[PDB]
Length: 495
Length: 16
Ligand SMILES: *[C@H]1O[C@H](CO)[C@H](O)[C@H](O)[C@H]1NC(C)=O
Ligand SMILES: *[C@H]1O[C@H](CO)[C@H](O)[C@H](O)[C@H]1NC(C)=O
Image (tube, rainbow over all chains, first blue to last red; front, side, top):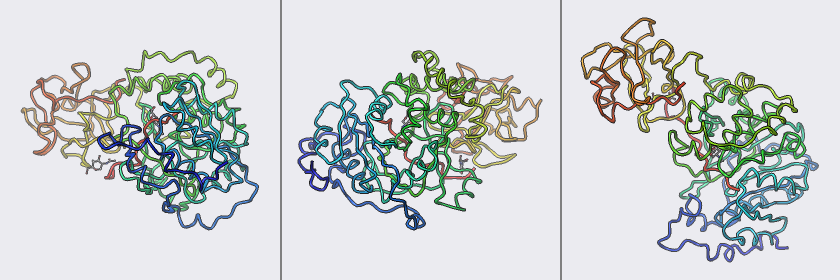
């Protein structure tokens, strides 16, 4: 019973402002000082393609229940999310906004917003996690279509109608906006490159893939066409409520930590639906990572329960490429999965090989006799061709997790191979630069082996190790094997 | 509830 323009933002943010000396980034990994400076209804630029302005929608699009789950969100950001939905959406299409407070420290963060028109608050009595919280919200939802948003988002002009139009036409489409960037430091709202879509490597964390030449050519042909995507990050999407329920909601055995990308993306595609990015729908999001999760590290274990629950149900034998990338996950308890395996059987879903061939053929699968695969990492750097060809030197370069010049395998024949080129010891004197040369099956100069717990790369039949100490002076070398940081190299997958 | 921290949409600044 307060209309949103009459909500007192100043009093709400209130005593939760950052005191001088307190870390502005402590509450939620973005600058709360800058978030608190903004008005709840602050103007943002219209990042849509100009062709999006030429669209008109029927008044009878199905209304949605917007479900926003949160845990210790910054009050200013939570309010601005809610206001953006209310300000930018035709009111008839917002049946309700359900805030699911997942046991935040202060119940007032959510409760005070319940005074706003259309906003209902459900508070969990313990921290349940995003997926269980979303099931609670979806169960409470009165509308025929569910919209899931995160708690630090800002909806743009006519963001909702394009999403609802897709789902009304075909209930098996699960659709997402193009996600614009709200800068974590200065809160400016900007658009990212149009040539990026969701993806993942074998470690199973969400990443952005650069579109292939074919995908980019297609996009240029119609920059406002819906784009099929192999994976959503899992934060923002719209789904017909009955389809959500029929397909198995979310797995209620998921915990708080991660994996919200995985299970739903695999299940929707394998069980006959699709995922889409809708370019005329724009929602900004406060992205919070500098650098997206890196392995090895503790992330592999932190996200393992939820990740294994997806992998063990959906991925068939391809789960073993995940365990090759994330060996720390192999023995992490993940709970019983018989209910979800029964669901998979009941729904007559396709195998994971079908997903890889038809939905994500860009994900490179190791050859069946590869010894190791992926990128060859040293700190945050990667073995890199530097765009060279035969007779060229090789280098190190910051790992960009985009494949390309950083894509390698240690083959059955013990070669370190990129396309048709192999690392070649052209000169055995210590200190000599190695070169790319065409792969030749019985060239002893092209044979390498992992040593010291798969932490170094030794040239077979020698006491020479791959060494980056020469990088500044021209490229990678062979050097007498020794206890050197510059001789540490590890493939992302050991098979 | 929360999502995990999401990566800013970026990729390599060179071409393969
Ligand atoms: C956060 O990280 C998890 C790790 O399991 C997933 O990659 C998830 O997709 C990420 N969430 C968002 C919103 O990017
Ligand atoms: C782009 O070129 C640089 C060297 O200039 C690196 O080789 C980098 O790995 C390349 N990017 C991709 C995606 O291959």
